[PDB]
Length: 98
Length: 98
Image (cartoon, rainbow over all chains, first blue to last red; front, side, top):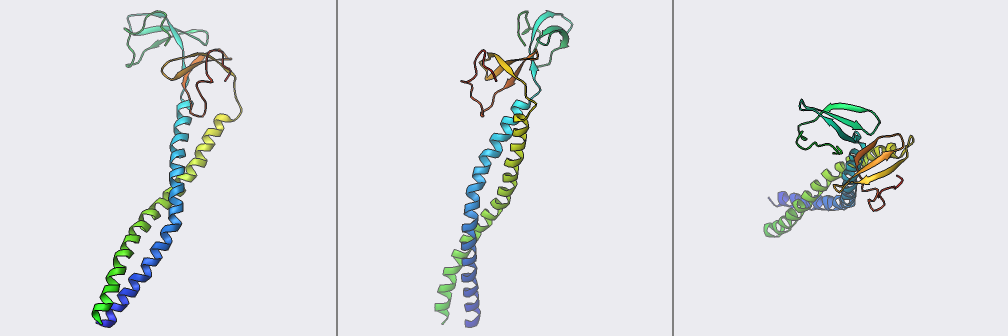
């Protein structure tokens, strides 16, 4: 009865202090989490963007109605390549750097 | 004295649980903190492979208005790749060693 309630009160009090004390130690940790969040995102994004396979420049030197477009590449030689579905043969005129 | 013992007991219960949620929140953050810190040091490795030798000189051929830069490499081919937020594009312009 009386004995029962006092033991509960003591035990709530005891653990209230334990959590309050721990909270502090991890508040310092949260501040750092945020710091690290900014950098996790910014670093990863700038590396993958530069790492991308170099998109070489060609100039639509010839064109055909069969899908093939002869692009004089800036490496030296010409290549005959077939264009994607993003770019269309309507967009590809002579003099068009691609 | 049942009245006395209850009043102290109810006082401590609410504070105890209030701190417990904060402790639980900030524990979870602790683990994520360590995971993300390891990732900033790993991402700095990716960054540092970009900074490492071999390196090749390029000179900027032109600036496209879409936020990409066309760089004529000293090998031959000019290539279109994205820009960084490490670098500035006010330092990039036609003839700009990079």
